[PDB]
Image (cartoon, rainbow over all chains, first blue to last red):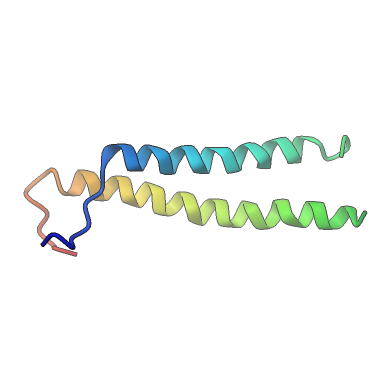
Length: 36
Length: 43
């Protein structure tokens, strides 16, 4: 019904973008094993 | 400065990253699962 759950194309994009940001801090923070 | 603490955070974020992504990939399948033949399951 109205209280149903519908996934939108955009909402999904925002989810991927959020995750991508986390990875950045992963590879970046990792690339500084000696720098940091 | 507990250098190990900094590395620990990276490892922790790495694990959650995999789980966080897993759900994302699954969600994508759900979208394509509702396109073909209705959506069979309602849940």
